Each structure stands twice: as structure tokens, then as C-alpha cells.
Image (cartoon, rainbow, N blue to C red):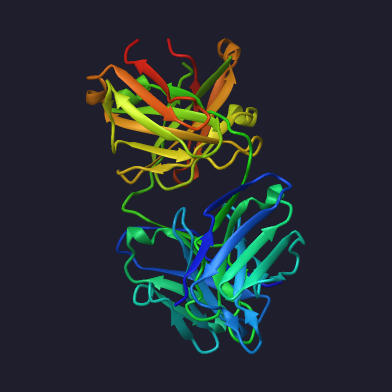
Amino acid sequence: EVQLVQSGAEVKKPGESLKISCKGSGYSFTSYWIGWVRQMPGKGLEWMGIIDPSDSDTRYSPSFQGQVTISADKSISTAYLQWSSLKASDTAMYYCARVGPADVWDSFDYWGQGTLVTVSSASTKGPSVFPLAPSGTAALGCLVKDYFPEPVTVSWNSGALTSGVHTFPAVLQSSGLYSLSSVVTVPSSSLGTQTYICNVNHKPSNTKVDKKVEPKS
Amino acid sequence: DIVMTQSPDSLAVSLGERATINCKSSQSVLLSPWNSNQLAWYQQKPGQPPKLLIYGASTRESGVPDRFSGSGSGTDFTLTISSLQAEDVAVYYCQQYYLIPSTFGQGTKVEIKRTVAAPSVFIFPPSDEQLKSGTASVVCLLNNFYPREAKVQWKVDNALQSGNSQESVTEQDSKDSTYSLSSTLTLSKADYEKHKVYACEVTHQGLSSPVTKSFNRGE
């Protein structure tokens, strides 16, 4: 089958150089053009440019020319996107995609899985976990504060409690650290007898915390 | 260049009913003498790469269900889903590939339509644990509402708070198709302890008038 395989997620600091890769297999890499597409967080797709791996004929969007370099190494069936000096504003998902076989131009028929690029001055840091204590339905939760980078996962009661759980998208604070809440709604009557524990795992820092959440005395 | 403009930005459709998305190009994308419109539609689900659905304006890609169809020509195009399935909830993009650059439309988010639901609102004071560290996060939760449009206003002793909160919203719930929202007001411990009444006021079409949840610090 045709596969475009991109290099893994990158967490970088402003001013650093970065080269990301897209390897095509299951077809002749030099027979199809490769495109790069940016998707900033929460935003749409942006066409960055295309390259013919046969001869490195490269066409850029005017929005990206001079900002990035697209290149290819046909000997290893790989295309690349690179920056000499990253900015925080380069934080985005980057896709490579194959231009289809039509005789003029074509749609993108196969896509890479994406490379997430996060650019920040912050360093790896595990969260602090605070209770959101319940005040016939009650809400309670956990505030998972001041961690970097994304993601963090939250479960409740070791996975036993799934109904009524909402784990929110993180917000990026002005400190450059993320914060997230996870909540659950439960019967008010259960608060005296049922234990509620949020299980937090911030894998990038290898930080696990189990936080019991109870009515405050 | 060619500018691609989609409409609407967001579309809510009942499960099993018809969904229709529009795409306009600023110039014709018709390639003569082949007389083919160089227009593609992609589907993108959260966390996933886009997937080609339709090319040449009206040709379904291999493996794509019959309920998807493309139409239109020149500068006006439409994607139709004849019967919306739960797996069709996604963002859809059009793209022209008539020339380079091969520009995309801005995307149309297709969501599940349901009945209006007012949010259930809850407020949470900062924990004593957090206060020890010098910061106070006050959280307001708006649970299981529809549609997505909602407004949270923070007041501390009747002073409107501006610029010192952040919020986020879940995607449509897997079970009930509602949204939830969490807003956090951040203050220093010192500022938190200078004030008494913390209030979150919520405006939503499911509510006759705004709902306020509050607490008094140290009660």
C-alpha cells in the first residue's frame, strides 16, 4: 500500500533549527509530487509548497517562501521541511501529502500522519493536582496545573468511573505552562459513601498523581 | 491567486438528515479542453489527517460511501451528505488545484443538531493546597449545554474581571451531543484574600435570564 510516514513530534525552543521528514513507500517516490501543509492549532489547512523529488523542482506559497526550505533526498524516498530559526508562531501540525497522478495538477490522494511541532521557551515540568471539591446531582473534579508539554491524561477511579466525565482541552497560560480541568457529575447522595479519585498521568515528565476529591470540612 | 470561501463556517444537522456545504472560488477552476473542475473535498476528524473524499468536483474517491456527493462548476461548488451518520461528524475542506498555489477553503465544521439544553452551572473555590503556593484558581463549570454559544462573566465583589480568565470547551459529547465549558479565573493569594464574593454569570439561549453562581470566601 502507499504510505507517507512522517518523523515524530518535536518540542523545540525559539531560535532552534529543525528539519522534519516524510518518507514515501509502496510507490515510486520520484513519480509524484509531495506537498507540505500547515495547520495551526484550531485553524484550517494552509498549502505551503510542493516538490518534485525527481529533480527537486520546488514551488512555494508566497506566504512561506523565504520562511522554510522544502527539499528531497530521492535516494531514500524522503522529502523534508526545515527552518533555520524557529519562532513560537511556528507551533502547528505539519502534514506532507502526495499529489495524485492527474496530467496537470491533482488533489492530495495520500497524507502523512502529521508532525506536531511545539515551539516554546518552557521546559518539561510535571503538574500540580488540586481538588475541585463538591459544593440530586453534584459536580467535582481535578485541576491539573502548570505542566509542559502536552498531553496529560486523566481517568477517574482507575477507569471504573467514565459516565459524566469531562476532561477539558488544556489552556496555555502566560507562563508558558498548560492547565487543564477534569470534572464528573455524580449523585449528591453518593458523596458520603463513594470515593472519587482522579488519576493523572503526565507521560512527558513521567509524573503520576492520584488525587482523592472529597467534600470539604 | 485563487481564494476559496466556504459557507457556513459551522453546520448542525440531525442524524440521518441531509447536510449541504458550499465552496466558492474567486476564479473559474475549470480546466479546458478536458472540461474538468479542479476542485477537491477533504474530510478531517479530530486528531487525524485529512482524507480525500471527492476530486474533480463530482468524482467520489475509492471506498467513499454513496451518501457523499459533489456538485457545481466554475466558481460555485457543493458537498452533500444525503443522510448524516455519526462517523460523518468532522471538518470539511475544499481545495482548488487548478493552479499553484493550490489553496484551501477555511473549513466547515459539521456537528450533530439536538434540542436546546441549558447549562448546569457550578463554581469551585481554590483549594487550601493551592493557596499555600501563592496562587488562586477559581473555576466555573458549564455542563452539558446546547448549542455551543455561551458567555461567562466573572465578578469579584461586583468588579467585572477582564483579561485574567481563560476558558475551554469540549467537543460534542459522545453520548448526548452537548458541550461543556470550563473557565478559570486566576488571582494571587494576596488578592484572593482581599475579596469576599466570587461570582460566575452565565448567558445561554437555554436560560430565560443569566444565571449566577457564587461563593463567599471563608464560609
- Which quarter of the image is occupied by the C terminus of chain A? top left
Residue found 40% across the figure and 32% down from its top? B152
Q: Is residue A67 above or below residue B20?
A: below
**Residue B40 location in percent, x, y?**
61, 70
Residue B51 showing in the rendered view: no
Q: Is residue B197 above or below residue A27?
A: above
Residue A61 vs residue A186: left or right?
left
**Residue B133 location in percent, x, y?**
29, 27
Residue found 29% across the figure and 23% down from its top? B156
Give the image quarter of residue A23. bottom right
Q: Nearer the viewer, residue B116 or A45?
A: B116
Q: Nearer the viewer, residue B195 or A167?
A: B195
Give the image quarter of residue B116. top right
Residue B72 vs residue A36: left or right?
right
Residue A22 showing in the rendered view: yes
Residue A50 vs residue B184: left or right?
right
Q: Is residue B171 above or below residue A84?
A: above
**Residue B186 location in percent, x, y?**
31, 32
- Which quarter of the image is occupied by the N terminus of chain A? bottom right
Q: Nearer the viewer, residue B107 or A6?
A: B107
Q: Is residue A75 above or below residue B23?
A: below
**Residue A65 location in percent, x, y?**
37, 77
Residue found 54% across the figure and 38% down from its top? B147
Q: Nearer the viewer, residue A92 or B45?
A: B45
